[PDB]
Image (cartoon, coloured by chain):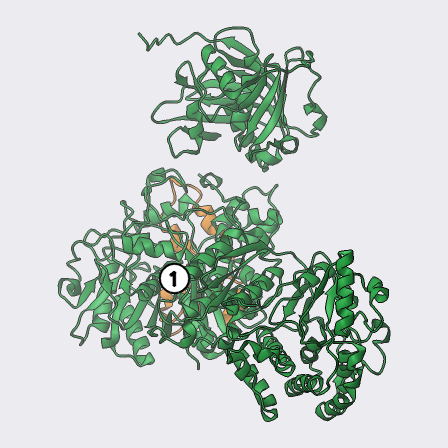
């Protein structure tokens, strides 16, 4: 069939957000297993404390993939992370994902768990339907097919711990047989349900130490880990980056075994190895590295390594290297194969084999390791070069083996175009993504294939990725440009300036691009028989070279044609063309009305015919007077020739009349500037004699005219007669009339639709000011070149970048020689450079949602999220805030009803704090919360002692009126002074309150203590405690009074979010009012009523003596 | 070299058996694991080929037939 290549790769692995972190850990030896308490409490049910745990599971860019917020919450974490990983993998290989939409690509996902689905279907009465369309195993690949629009098969294998490699093998077979052009093979595994770990523990597969000491005597069993990995398998004809070539891949099962289903058989593994390598036609001597399964079991390791020895070490002298990524990252059950593939491919990319951890002495039951035939990579070793093999054996019996040929592509030899600046274009969700891609490209400005791949993946629609930026590399005056992209398509227009724009040495900077030089040479061929060559003028060094009219016109038209040729390479078809009279020849080119040869010859003949005719010198000057005003102001024999804009209207005529008009304007003071054209007044009645010879010559030149497109807007003939015969098709008559009839440029500019993206196609952006004023305010001029600029190529690339920032998609790769593929080895990974919009935090099921009242562990340790409690020190000892209990009850009620706290307005009633809980300096205090939904009552207990009691229930009908601030009893009109934060907390300290920084929230408070402002952060406890502090501040009583009862508390989160108003800084604040007459403390969306505080005796610890 | 392609889209027995952390038997996984819907058949009948448990919903059986 056809070759199958690993073209891309992406994945999240333990303690590593991207493959770059995975490699940084592999080489550096950082063990990726940890003793954290993330998934569940360590030691629960006797399980090992160690496990492979991903850094996060709650980040997901829902808006990108079109998942509504309600569906995103119920979606499986594996599915979300796999969608992101798959997109990262597809763009890793330089393939724009849109180039695969609508094709026959397939999705094979190896998944062996549905914990989230079980968690979401626990409560039959409140379960939501879409939980099934996001938690089913089938959707693990069907969602990918739906979003990416792959028409190939969508299968979700299980195959009992070999799912990833089995999916890889199925994709390989599909691509080999021609059923599919490409495949997306992914592996997913997340540890959420402790009961599965307990089952594996009972089977004896796990290890008490959580270390997979593969290939070692102390091997006992593996430690479960997590991992989401995706690879892009494509046929060679469609790939850009080649990590390796799958020479052959196969699967077989152990069959029947006497010992049991779960006992591995080495004979079957040996047979699989031998069959695949023989079928591929390889020789065992070629293999250099074998990525063993390497679980680390007393039984599995001998079987597997003896199989590898009997299969590949039969007759080879030099030893065979062995490795196992499970020593580092643990064992991802279904995703194990793809993790090993990632390790192997990264090792090949960097030219080193990552060291294996936890290997000191070999297993005495493996003769190979004790001998020298089989060697383990205990320290980094350079890659000498050879084939590689990967084997993944599930405990059910399924065996998978793949043979990889590493990509050995030498770096491209230096070429002349290497020095030339190359343009880079990036698109992204957030400015950070664009800046990351730009910086990565900047660090590698000399990597042509890398820059081409980046430029390929950046052509994503602006709606999906509203941030774009360009960074011209290799230029001395270079830097990133980043700006937001407006939505909606914007028209692309062209402008071709007149005969004024000309300078000595134009086009040399652009002569280096192949397309431009080819176009200039074609123009020279068009003009060669006449007697001049455009390139001769360009390479020339005389200032007077271009002061000849014929030379000027020929060179200008040739350069404009070259610019249009460069534009057409990138795929830009103008939606409107409008040019000044020398320019229209080029405008004729833009629409296909004029052939290149015709246009160049026409320019030469215009220049000549102007040359032959001898007329009295006539100076054309543009004066700052309105077109209509110049109509009468223009002296007899002088007419307004060009209508540049409303402010400025060019006028031409005899040199003496024009000088007289200039003098008169100087007397008036109006802007009277005289241009230089060698005493020639264009678009004036003087040229009326030139036409006849020009008429004949052009009739000879343009043989069969062509229709004028609706895009072109002729400024030679007013808009009234745009349907006449004269302007129906370009010909000698049209060009002659343009050379004679006055220019109506201002008339056409009005027709440019609002939000257009204009391009000034000319050697100099002379009409930049004219376009900036005349055209509507919201249009972008985008000039291609500049006069006397040292390197016009950089300016042109910057102009293309500004096109990129306007929405129009142009590819700068077409402007340079193509990059042969596959790309050279060592081309940097692109997957790590992609970043998403992870502002939101979606739900991930907890370990207490599966079968086994609510209990909360208050750990004040540094890492614990409850660390802020260490600032609630009263009497010199840390106490749990009274409002802390309310948050616990709120969360428990929210979990009971099924809502979140932000979505659950609550009403506490008759709260009694029976005793105070002291938070120990070391350790934890466990608080239980019990509810009686029928009675609407709650009890918080601590070691069997009652702590808090009261009533809690959802607020059926919140009323925002309840939080309107009562009119203060004291007008306080003067308000001369107010207490700052420092002063309020100094007073509280003197009373005996030692609140730390976290529990300091009163930005200001009135002298009477009846009003103020409460700072808002993500924490409710701090906010409500600051309300209680405001209540206490105005009290005259001395000594620290602590709450003992509350009669009513209302929380309405919606009104709260509406009440917050940001200060001039970035801080969010809420106004507070305390009414001691009414016994209400109302601040933001909270309402405390009937607070009672009782004096607490001072601890008399009297630590000071 | 015979192979087994079994179309299964449910693991209810896995959930019921693994509800009690302090009484769950180890071999509940062998008989209730989804992949065991084909590996067990291969083990008993001594089939040395593929053993895969597809998961496409409403079409797992016919997808297995196609494979």
- A959 shown above or below A612: above
Q: Which residue sits at x=78%, y=62%?
A: A664
Side of A51 relative to A772 (left or right): left
Using the image, determine if residue A28 lies above or below residue A460. above
Q: Which chain is green?
A: A
Left or right: A300, with A532 as reference point: left
Q: Chain of mark 1?
A: A
The residue at the point 42 percent across, 8 percent down is A1098
Of the 4 image quadrants, the one containing the C terminus of chain A is top left
Along the line of sight, which residue is nearer the eye, A606 or B60? Answer: A606
- The answer to whether A732 is drawn above or below residue A33 in the figure is below
| Count of numbered marks | 1
Identify residue for label 1. A338
Query: What is the x, y in percent for residue A440?
Result: 43, 59
Instruction: Identify which residue, A184 or A617, lies in the foreground.
Output: A617
Q: Is residue A947 visible?
A: yes
**In front of the other: A1087 or A470:** A470
Specify the quadrant that holds the N terminus of chain A. bottom left
Residue A831 screen position, x and y as percent: 44, 60
Q: Secondary structure at mark 1?
A: helix
Residue depicted at 51% across the width and 9% down the height:
A1094
Q: Left or right of A524: which side holds A1? A: left
Who's orange, chain-wise? B
């Amino acid at each position: 069939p056809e070759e199958v290549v690993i073209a891309g790769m992406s994945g999240k692995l333990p303690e590593s957000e991207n493959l770059q972190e995975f490699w940084d850990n592999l080489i550096g030896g950082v063990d990726m297993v940890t003793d954290d308490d993330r998934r569940w409490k360590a030691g629960l049910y006797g399980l090992p404390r160690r496990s492979g745990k991903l850094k996060d599971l709650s980040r997901f860019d829902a808006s990108f993939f079109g998942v509504h917020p309600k569906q995103a919450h119920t979606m499986d974490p594996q599915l979300r992370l796999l969608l992101e990983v798959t997109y990262e993998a597809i763009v890793d290989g330089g393939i724009n994902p849109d180039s695969l939409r609508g094709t026959h690509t397939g999705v094979w996902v190896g998944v062996s768990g549905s914990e989230t689905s079980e968690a979401l279907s626990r409560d039959p009465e409140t379960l939501v339907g879409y939980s099934m369309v996001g938690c089913q195993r089938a959707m693990m690949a069907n969602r990918l097919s739906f979003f990416f629009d792959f028409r190939g098969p969508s299968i979700a294998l299980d195959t009992a711990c070999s799912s990833s490699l089995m999916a890889l093998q199925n994709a390989y077979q599909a691509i080999h047989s021609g059923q599919c052009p490409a495949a997306i093979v992914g592996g997913i595994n997340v540890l959420l349900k402790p009961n599965t770990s307990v089952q594996f523990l009972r089977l004896g597969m796990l290890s008490p130490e959580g270390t997979c000491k593969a290939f070692d005597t102390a091997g006992n069993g593996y430690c479960r880990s997590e991992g989401v990995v995706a690879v892009l398998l494509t046929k060679k004809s469609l790939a850009r980056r080649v990590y390796a070539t799958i020479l052959n891949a196969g699967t077989n099962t152990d069959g029947f075994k006497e010992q049991g289903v779960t006992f591995p058989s080495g004979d079957i593994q040996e047979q699989l190895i031998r069959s695949l390598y023989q079928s591929a036609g390889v020789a065992p001597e070629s293999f250099e590295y074998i990525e063993a399964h390497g679980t680390g079991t007393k039984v599995g390791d001998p079987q597997e390594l003896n199989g590898i020895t009997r299969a590949l070490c039969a007759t080879r002298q030099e030893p065979l290297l062995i490795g196992s990524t499970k020593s580092n990252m643990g064992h991802p059950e279904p995703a194990s194969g793809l993790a090993a593939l990632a390790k192997v491919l990264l090792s090949l990319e960097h030219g080193l084999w990552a060291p294996n951890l936890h290997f000191h002495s070999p297993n005495p039951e493996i003769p190979a390791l004790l001998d020298g035939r089989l060697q383990v990579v205990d320290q980094p070793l350079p890659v000498r070069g050879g084939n590689v093999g990967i084997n993944s054996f599930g405990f059910g019996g399924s065996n998978v083996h793949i043979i990889l040929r590493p990509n050995t592509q030498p770096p491209p030899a230096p070429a002349p175009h290497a020095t030339l600046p190359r343009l880079l274009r990036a698109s992204g969700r957030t400015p950070e993504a664009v800046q990351k891609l730009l910086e990565q490209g900047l660090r590698h400005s000399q990597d042509l294939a890398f820059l081409s791949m980046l430029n390929d993946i950046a052509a994503v629609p602006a709606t999906a990725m509203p941030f774009r930026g360009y960074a011209v590399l290799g230029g001395e005056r270079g830097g990133p440009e980043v700006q937001q992209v407006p939505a909606g398509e914007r028209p692309l227009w062209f402008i071709c300036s007149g005969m004024g724009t000309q300078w000595r040495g134009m086009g040399l900077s652009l002569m280096r691009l192949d397309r431009f030089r080819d176009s200039i040479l074609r123009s020279d061929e068009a003009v060669k028989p006449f007697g001049l060559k455009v390139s001769q003028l360009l390479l020339s060094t005389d200032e007077s070279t271009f002061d000849d009219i014929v030379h000027s016109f020929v060179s200008l038209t040739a350069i404009q044609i070259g610019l249009i040729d460069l534009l057409s390479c990138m795929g830009l078809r103008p939606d409107g063309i409008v040019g000044h009279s020398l320019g229209e020849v080029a405008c004729g080119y833009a629409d296909g009305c004029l052939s290149q040869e015709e246009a160049v010859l026409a320019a030469y003949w215009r220049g000549q015919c102007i040359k032959e005719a001898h007329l009295p010198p006539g100076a054309m000057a543009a004066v700052g007077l309105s077109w209509e005003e110049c109509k009468q102001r223009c002296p007899p024999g002088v007419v307004p020739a060009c209508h540049n804009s409303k402010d400025t209207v060019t006028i031409s005529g005899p040199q003496a009349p024009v000088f007289e008009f200039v003098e008169q304007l100087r007397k008036e003071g109006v802007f009277a500037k005289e241009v230089r054209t060698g005493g020639m007044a264009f678009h004036s009645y003087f040229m009326e004699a030139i036409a006849p010879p020009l008429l004949q010559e052009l009739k000879k030149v343009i043989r069969e005219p062509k229709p004028r497109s609706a895009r072109w807007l002729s400024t030679s003939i007013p808009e009234a007669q745009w349907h006449s015969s004269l302007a129906r098709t370009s010909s000698a008559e049209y060009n002659v009339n343009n050379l004679v009839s006055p220019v109506l440029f201002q008339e056409a500019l009005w027709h440019v639709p609002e939000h257009a993206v204009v391009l000034e196609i000319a050697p100099h952006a002379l009409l930049q000011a004219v376009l900036k004023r005349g055209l509507k305010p919201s249009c972008t001029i985008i000039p291609l070149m500049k006069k006397d600029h040292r390197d016009n190529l950089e300016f042109f690339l910057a102009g293309i970048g500004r096109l990129h920032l306007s929405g129009i998609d142009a590819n700068p790769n077409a402007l340079f020689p193509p990059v042969e593929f596959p790309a050279p080895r060592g081309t940097p990974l692109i997957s790590p450079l992609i970043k998403w919009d992870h502002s939101l935090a979606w739900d991930v099921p907890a370990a207490e949602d599966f079968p086994n009242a609510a209990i909360y562990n208050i750990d004040t340790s540094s890492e614990s999220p409850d660390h802020y409690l260490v600032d609630h020190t009263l009497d010199g000892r840390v106490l749990f805030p009274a409002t802390g209990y309310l948050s616990i009850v709120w969360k428990t009620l929210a979990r009971a009803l099924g809502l979140g706290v932000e979505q659950l307005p609550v009403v506490f009633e008759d709260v009694v704090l029976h005793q105070a809980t002291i938070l120990p300096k070391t350790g934890t205090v466990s608080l239980e919360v019990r509810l009686l939904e029928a009675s609407r009552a709650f009890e918080v207990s601590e070691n069997g002692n009652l702590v808090v009691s009261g009533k809690v229930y959802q607020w059926d009908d919140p009323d925002p009126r309840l939080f309107d601030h009562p009119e203060s009893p004291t007008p306080n009109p003067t308000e001369p002074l107010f207490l700052a934060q420092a002063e309020v907390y100094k007073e509280l300290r003197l009373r005996g309150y030692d609140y730390g920084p976290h529990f300091q929230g009163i930005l200001e408070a009135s002298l009477e203590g009846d009003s103020g402002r409460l700072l808002w952060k993500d924490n409710w406890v701090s906010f409500m405690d600051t309300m209680l502090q405001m209540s206490i501040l105005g009290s005259a009583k001395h000594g620290l009074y602590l709450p003992t009862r509350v009669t009513a508390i209302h929380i309405d989160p919606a009104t709260h979010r509406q009440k917050l108003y940001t200060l001039q800084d970035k801080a969010q604040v809420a106004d507070v009012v305390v009414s001691r007459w009414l016994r209400v403390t109302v601040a933001g969306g909270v309402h405390i009523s009937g607070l009672h505080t009782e004096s607490a005796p001072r601890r008399q610890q009297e630590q000071q003596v």
